[PDB]
Amino acid sequence: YPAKPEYPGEDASPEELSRYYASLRHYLNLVTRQRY
């Protein structure tokens, strides 16, 4: 589980959280290239 933080939810702003979402998606986008 390379960097698997928990999501905030609908607590933060619709833009601020949307930015943070990139860090979450980036993790998955790093797992979408499994090797060995």
Image (cartoon, rainbow, N blue to C red):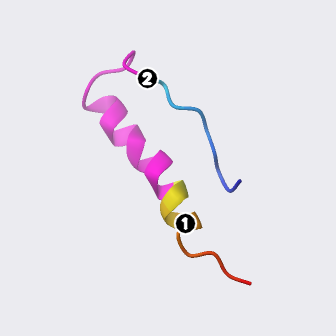
Is 10 positioned to the left or the right of 25 in the image? Answer: left
Residue type, mark 2 in image: Gly
Q: Which of 35 and 17 is in front in this view?
A: 35
Q: Which of 11 and 31 is in front in this view?
A: 31
Q: Which residue lies furthest to the right in this view?
A: 36
Residue stretch in magenta: 9-26
Residue 5 got which mark? none
* Quadrant in which the C terminus appears: bottom right
Helix, strand, or loop for circle 1? helix
Q: Residue furthest bottom?
A: 36
Q: In which quarter of the image is residue 16?
A: top left
Q: Mark 2 points at which residue?
A: 9
Q: Quadrant of residue 5?
A: top right
Residue type, mark 1 in image: Leu
What x and y, as percent, mark residue 35? 67, 81
The residue depicted at 58 percent of the width and 65 percent of the height is 31
Q: Name the residue under label 1.
A: 30
Q: Answer with mark 1 or mark 2, whichever residue precedes in sequence.
A: 2
Q: In this view, does 34 lie above or below 3?
A: below
Q: Residue furthest left?
A: 15
Q: Is residue 33 above or below residue 22?
A: below
What x and y, as percent, mark residue 26? 47, 57
What distance separates the C-alpha of mark 1 from that of mark 2? 22 Å
Number of other residues with Cα within 10 Å of mark 1, as a class: few under 14, some 14 to 19, many 20 or more: few
Number of other residues with Cα within 10 Å of mark 2, as a class: few under 14, some 14 to 19, many 20 or more: few
The residue depicted at 37 percent of the width and 19 percent of the height is 10
Look at the numbered discs 1 and 2 and tell me whether their residues touch, using CB distance below 8 Å. no
Q: In this view, does 33 lie above or below 12?
A: below
- On whether residue 20 falls in the magenta region, the answer is yes
Secondary structure mostly taken by the magenta-highlighted segment of the chain: helix
What x and y, as percent, mark residue 8? 48, 25
